[PDB]
Image (cartoon, grey):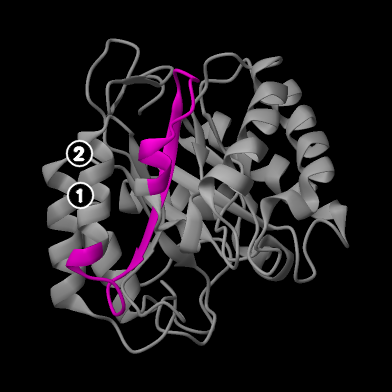
Amino acid sequence: TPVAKNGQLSIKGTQLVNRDGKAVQLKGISSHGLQWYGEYVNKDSLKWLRDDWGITVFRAAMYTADGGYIDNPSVKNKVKEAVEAAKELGIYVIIDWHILNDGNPNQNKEKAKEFFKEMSSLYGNTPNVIYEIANEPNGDVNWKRDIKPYAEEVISVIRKNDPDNIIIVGTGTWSQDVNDAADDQLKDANVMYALHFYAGTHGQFLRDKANYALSKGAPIFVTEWGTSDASGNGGVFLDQSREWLKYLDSKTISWVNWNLSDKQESSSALKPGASKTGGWRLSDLSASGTFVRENILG
């Protein structure tokens, strides 16, 4: 199992590497918002994904807004649950401070810093953990004015308890505007920038900004991508999805598919009715779910 095999991750240039300094490409899946679908996120289902799908990373998508942590912080217990499972299973785990309607990460910066102080404190001696501090900036929200200053403060409070675990920072326009990041990069040695795409929506233009970012030295991590369109629908777009994953392989970019749930949308891995604890029949999986599993089992 990884972490037992790769240990603690760091960044060599653009390439995510293991403790040996080997190139590593994590592949996995994200929960839906933990406030609605945390029932699917537990040591059993995570175990099933590890054992049946070969996932090497699980993302715990803790919405801040929309009935999430700001209004009900007890959801932090689901993050802690998933993390303990990940440590116990030898897989990596992303703690995703999942902004969306609160499109400016500054809106909730005080609560975000307090949240990350506790997590880095609890888990910062843990090689499993990756922090994702701001899922998707959007609106009149840009790198230089809004996202960078936030990242320095939040980063500064994480590094106190955890100096070396990977931190992934979202970018503008729903974690598309990596080029703006790529120009005015942070100094932290273990920071990556998030790139999100949907196969039914995003095409070559988004890949080019990504190419531009790498060429300027900014590492990229796909903390969220879907085989559906950006709404999370439109059916399951196999040509573009195949085309995207081909591109990501070519640069050894780690990725996390959206999403593990039985929600009634195209992006869901599961068909309605699917067990919360795994042990899923091949039929229980959606058209999306099947494709994603096939692309992790190599």
Residue 213, image quadrant: top left
Q: Is residue 95 visible?
A: no
Q: Find residue 214 and name its label.
A: none
Residue range in magenta is: 180-205
- Image coordinates for residue 8, horizontal then vertical, percent: 44, 17
Residue 118 is left or right of residue 2, and the answer is: right
- Viewer-proximal residue among 233 and 57: 233
- Magenta stretch containing residue 24, yes or no? no
Task: From this view, report whether residue 191 is shown above or below residue 85.
Answer: above
Q: Are marks 2 and 1 in contact (CB under 8 Å)?
A: yes
Give the residue drawn at x 35%, y 64%.
Answer: 197
Q: Amino acid at mark 2?
A: Thr
Q: Amino acid at mark 1?
A: Leu
- Magenta stretch containing residue 199, yes or no? yes
Residue 185 is left or right of residue 41, and the answer is: left
- Image coordinates for residue 82, horizontal then vertical, percent: 63, 44
Q: CA distance from mark 2 to mark 1?
A: 6 Å
Determine which residue is flagged by label 1: 248
